[PDB]
RNA sequence: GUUUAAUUCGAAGCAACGCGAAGAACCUUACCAGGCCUUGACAUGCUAGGGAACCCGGGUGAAAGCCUGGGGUGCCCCGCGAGGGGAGCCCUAGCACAGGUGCUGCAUGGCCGUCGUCAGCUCGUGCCGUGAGGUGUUGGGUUAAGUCCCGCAACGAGCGCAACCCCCGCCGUUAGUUGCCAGCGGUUCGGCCGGGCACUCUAACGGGACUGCCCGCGAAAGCGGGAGGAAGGAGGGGACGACGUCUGGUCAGCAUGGCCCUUACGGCCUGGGCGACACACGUGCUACAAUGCCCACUACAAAGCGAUGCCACCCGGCAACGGGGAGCUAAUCGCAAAAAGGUGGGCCCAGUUCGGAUUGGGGUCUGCAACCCGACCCCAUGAAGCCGGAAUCGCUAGUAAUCGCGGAUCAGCCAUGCCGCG
């Protein structure tokens, strides 16, 4: 009666749950409209709809789990498309060529000994 | 019913043991939900390689502790015999809680 | 910061309370410092070491919360 | 002061006032761990050896 | 000077530890405490037989100690007035389940320390280094081995200088994991002083 | 001396555990 | 940076308008790793010329851009046995990147207490040809095309 | 460097200078001053007196040390008995002795750094040369690379690059004390419950990426691609550091030759010192502000840690904190509140509601004890600081900057430095 999506970027977790509704899109309660009040990338989290000309259509339950805020958004920009394909699989050639169906993994670098912020070596003094 | 975890710094000695315990009941009594892998706990120790001035060039060690869990759903009076009978394990410690 | 309770070293009272069975003298040669300047003792002079010698001072009413180790300077530069 | 200081770290004299540590084999003062009782030296020259259970060399 | 401890690089894989037991939180040192003197007790008492390894089996209360020596005919005693009295006289510091083993050795000259043990023993006596290793790194390879390497350094000839030495034939891929190479730690107190006798013995793969 | 013996300055150099911190 | 000629990063276009050029500028004003805090300035400025006049804040943006992209410029280069400077044209991509960083750094100089004020002005004042970003633009050409005589290297 | 009595020693361009220190209030401590001890603070062995062992105390003495006291009196060769002996342990005397952070890293072992993650170091056969030796490793091209290709009197290999190891990107299974109304039944409408294991998450083994295919280019390796695929040409980090130079660094982590010290160059205590300051440099910390600064309200972590410890919570406290005490020997309990973020009001350019150095007074908070030589907080005092010369530093991607969260030694103690996390 619905389709599920997974979305992990920058070690974030945001369970994505698509249903065929009309206009309910919230997150753990709160309200995605106003959970994310004051953003800029906010519209960018729902992109695979206006790019498929189908925003005024389905509905979405959302669960997030930890992770970074932008990483919480950028992961949502996946589980949408990382759903639907189960019984709505023709949603591909107007996505992957345009370039959405990818994790874009960019995990941080760990701090390393003998350095500072992982790659900034200390000041160097020949004198 | 009775509760046991399994703690070992090496999963190979732990998983096998965890696979070993299942033999003394799951093939002695009712089915048992398989091992329950806890998130592995680490004791992360990084030490300066050098013995003197060279403070950098350090090297890192870990004393990982792999924790796993097994719960029996029907404590069978005959299977428990098969437990203590298994006095051939490995260098791993386990506890029994109620 | 001397909280609920103040202090002063033991043999000090040995070396300073016998100075009052008759309100006694002033001469002394001891070895403590971290003690508290005793409001009940603003009437003597106390031998306080520095590093090589004991350098004392006449005690004065105002000296209370401060420590006996301040009147004996150590790093001879000033 | 090699064989003269560790002995002090036994009798426990003055109050909780001089309670410090001491590596076993290396007998070294600081850089000692309360887990192994070994200086950062007297640990490696057994860690790399292997007399230190589960103490592999990290990697991540 | 580089190349960190090959075994120290092995360790957590291939060759497993020279001991074996889990330990709890605050009982680790408490067990390690007397665990080390167990080894330290024998590395000059059990020596005249060629010691190369000593496991430690524990889990709780009972301790099983297994030794790996090549010449057991003297550590065992004329009938037990050694191996069975070494156990009893071992609890005196650690009242534990006194257990022992003695694993045989079919080919001594294939364990890295035993060479370095033999070399230092041979180095102590006024012997020809360069031509006590050449014989050695050959009889290693002779005993079915397939690679070796035995480096020593110190006061060769007692001269004021201190050049190391070489004696090797074949492949010793130290940097590879599956190689399985044992490593020898020796020591030689001498007339002039202290030496440094090492040894690598490649063995196989997979 | 930030974080040592007898002043008042600052403790992002001395720590605080065991110092005066709650134990039991 | 000697052998292979590297790869130009390709950027995420804007959401509001439909052009990479927009994002190409908002990330440029971004400081201290503060991203949303920058698009306000831009879009708060956008929502001024909408009220200033019937000039769309984008369909004008690009004109001062083409009023800040120069043509030919100099470059310091060592020859002979001392130090001189060499002129040339301008790489088109560089011409673009040169413009943006020219634009933003003109903000903080403008005497404006708030924020987006520092933005739109240097944009607008350069929409006809009387802006700071124009001065520093032509000055290079003033420092460049005055060196027409260096006709041997050039390449 | 300067000085004090001591300001212990080492470290010396790149390889020293938030380095040995991941523990300079006393001890740590190695330095100074004074007091005292000399078979000891330690180990093995012998002789003699008293005694077993071992607990407790006092006077004095700064402490140590010195003197003294009460008890108590074991295990083995005899003898019930008055009484002989012995092993261990302790104190007092003679010893053998040990002991020293004393010296030489230019006498060493081990360990470490640099070149340097540079890409080189070589062998077997053959060939050229009387021979040492050369070739192979050189030439063109390519790459991170002696990586690889063409050619080449050379052809192959070993050490090294890589790869086999670890963490992340994807997925499958196993397994469900975290999680879940994604479907239902009670809900103080909390995942609290019944309940379930797809999903979340966790940790074991595995498939997967090999220029595999296709459109072209350069013969060749290789290149512009493109599709599929999560990722495509090494996907991105870790650990791994060859032959060898630096007669490199370390007798101060340790062992050790040789010289020396042994009534002290050994040992214990109180105090003082490495924090001393006309100066100068190294590495960092806040800034010198409107993308800014305060106040109130409103969400998201990743990792790490802890029972004789972590501290919810209740009250008290105008605050660091105090009394009581839930839970947790640990995916449960907690440390723990994360900041930038969003809303809303103020401040409208000022030396400022920017910054907190100094300093007066006042506090709680750990331990025998907090002046030189602790925080946090209150009333303030509120300095220079308006972007910095010659120069010079790191950084090619989730990197740079910015914002915050842990760990490691510990009775307290050098933890804004270090190592990890987001
Ligand atoms: Mg391995
Ligand atoms: Mg992916
Ligand atoms: Mg050297
Ligand atoms: Mg601040
Ligand atoms: Mg407050």
Image: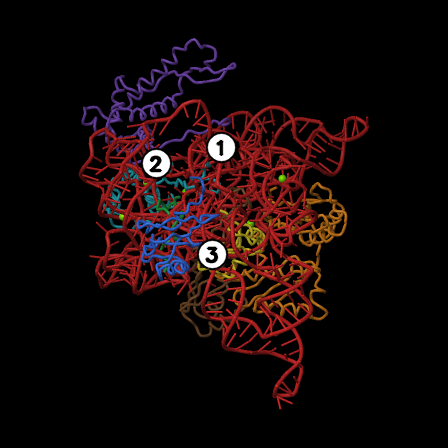
Chain colours: A cyan, B brown, C blue, D yellow, E orange, F green, G purple, H red
Residue located farthest toward the top when viewing the structure as drawn: G149
Q: What is the x, y in percent for residue A67?
A: 35, 46
Q: Is residue A27 visible?
A: no
> From the image, which quarter does the N terminus of chain B lie in?
bottom left
Rendered residue at 39%/40% (across/down): A102
- Name above or below for residue H21 compared with residue H396: below
Same chain under badges 3 and 2? The reply is: no
* 10 Å crowding of disc 1: few (<14), some (14-19), many (20+): few
* 10 Å crowding of disc 2: few (<14), some (14-19), many (20+): few
Q: Is mark 3 within 8 Å of ligand 5?
A: no
Q: Report the chain holding disc 2.
A: G
Q: Is residue C70 visible?
A: yes
Q: Report the chain holding disc 3.
A: D
**Residue B35 vs residue D25: left or right?**
left
**Residue A12 vs residue H106: left or right?**
left
Mark sitting on residue G33:
2
Which residue is the site of mark 1?
Answer: A125
> From the image, which quarter does the C terminus of chain B lie in?
bottom left
Residue C31, quarter of the rendered image: bottom left
Same chain under badges 2 and 1? The reply is: no
Which residue is the site of mark 3?
Answer: D18
**In terms of depth relative to the viewer, which is nearer, D32 or G93?**
D32
**SS label for mark 1:** loop
């Amino acid at each position: 009666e619905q389709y599920y999506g997974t979305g992990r970027r920058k070690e974030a977790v945001a369970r994505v749950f698509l249903r065929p509704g009309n206009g309910k899109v919230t997150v753990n309660g709160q309200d995605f409209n106003e959970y994310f009040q004051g953003l800029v990338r906010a519209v960018a989290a729902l992109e695979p709809l206006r790019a498929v000309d189908a925003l005024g259509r389905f509905d979405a339950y959302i669960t997030v789990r930890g992770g970074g805020k932008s990483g919480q958004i950028d992961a949502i920009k996946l589980g949408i498309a990382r759903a639907l394909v189960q019984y709505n699989p023709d949603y591909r050639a107007k996505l992957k060529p345009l370039g959405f169906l990818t994790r874009d993994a960019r995990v941080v670098e760990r701090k390393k000994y003998g350095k500072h912020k992982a790659r900034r070596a200390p000041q160097y003094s020949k004198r | 019913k009775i509760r046991i975890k399994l703690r070992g710094f090496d999963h190979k000695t732990l998983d096998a043991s965890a696979q070993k315990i299942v033999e003394a009941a799951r093939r002695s009594g009712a089915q048992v939900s398989g091992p329950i892998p806890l998130p592995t706990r680490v004791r992360r120790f990084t030490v300066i390689r050098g013995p003197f001035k060279h403070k950098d060039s350090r090297e890192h060690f870990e004393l990982r502790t792999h924790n796993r869990l097994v719960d029996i759903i029907n404590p069978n009076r005959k299977t428990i015999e098969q437990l203590m009978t298994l006095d051939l394990p490995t260098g791993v410690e386990i506890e029994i809680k109620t | 910061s001397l909280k609920k309770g103040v202090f002063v070293d033991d043999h000090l009272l040995e070396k300073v309370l016998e100075l009052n069975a008759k309100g006694e003298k002033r001469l002394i040669k001891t070895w403590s410092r971290r003690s508290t300047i005793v409001p009940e003792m603003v009437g003597h002079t106390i031998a306080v070491y520095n590093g090589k010698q004991h350098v004392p001072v006449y005690i004065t009413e105002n000296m209370v919360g401060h420590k006996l180790g301040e009147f004996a300077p150590t790093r001879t530069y000033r | 002061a090699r064989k003269a200081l560790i002995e002090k770290a036994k009798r426990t004299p003055k109050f909780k006032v001089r309670a410090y540590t001491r590596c076993v084999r290396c007998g070294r003062a600081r850089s000692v761990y309360r887990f192994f009782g070994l200086c950062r030296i007297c640990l490696r020259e057994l860690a790399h050896k292997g007399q230190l259970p589960g103490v592999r060399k990290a990697s991540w | 000077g580089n190349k960190i401890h090959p075994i120290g690089f092995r360790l957590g894989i291939t060759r497993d530890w020279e001991s074996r037991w889990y330990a709890g939180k605050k009982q680790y040192r408490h067990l390690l405490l007397e665990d080390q003197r167990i080894r330290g007790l024998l590395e000059k008492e059990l020596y005249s037989a060629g010691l190369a390894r000593v496991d430690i089996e524990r889990a709780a209360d009972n301790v099983a100690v297994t030794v790996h020596v090549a010449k057991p005919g003297v550590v065992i005693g004329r009938g037990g007035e050694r191996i069975r009295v070494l156990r009893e006289e071992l609890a005196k510091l650690t009242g534990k389940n006194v257990a022992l083993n003695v694993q045989e050795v079919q080919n001594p000259n294939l364990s890295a320390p035993l060479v370095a043990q033999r070399v230092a023993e041979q180095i102590e006596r006024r012997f020809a280094v360069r031509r006590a290793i050449k014989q050695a790194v050959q009889r290693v390879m002779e005993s079915g081995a397939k690679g070796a390497k035995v480096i020593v350094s110190g006061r060769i000839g007692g001269a004021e200088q201190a050049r190391t030495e070489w004696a090797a034939q074949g492949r010793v891929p130290l940097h590879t994991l599956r190689a399985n190479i044992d490593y020898g730690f020796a020591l030689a107190r001498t007339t002039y002083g202290v030496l440094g006798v090492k040894a690598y013995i490649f063995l196989g793969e997979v | 001396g930030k974080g040592d013996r007898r002043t008042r300055r600052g403790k992002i150099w001395r720590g605080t555990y065991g110092k005066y911190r709650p134990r039991k | 940076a000697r052998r292979r000629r590297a790869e130009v990063r390709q950027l995420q276009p804007d959401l509001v308008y439909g052009d990479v050029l927009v994002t190409a500028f908002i990330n440029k004003i971004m400081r201290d790793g503060k991203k949303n805090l920058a698009a306000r300035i831009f879009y708060d400025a956008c929502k001024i010329i909408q009220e200033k006049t019937g000039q769309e804040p984008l369909k004008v943006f690009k004109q001062a851009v083409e009023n800040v992209k120069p043509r030919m410029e100099v470059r310091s280069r060592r020859v002979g046995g001392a130090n001189y400077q060499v002129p040339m044209e301008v790489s088109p991509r560089r011409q673009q990147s040169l413009a943006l960083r020219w634009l933003v750094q003109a903000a903080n100089q403008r005497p404006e207490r708030r924020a987006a004020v520092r933005i739109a002005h240097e944009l607008m004042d350069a929409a006809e040809g009387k802006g700071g970003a124009v001065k520093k633009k032509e000055d290079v050409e003033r420092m460049a095309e005055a060196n027409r005589a260096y006709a041997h290297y050039r390449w």
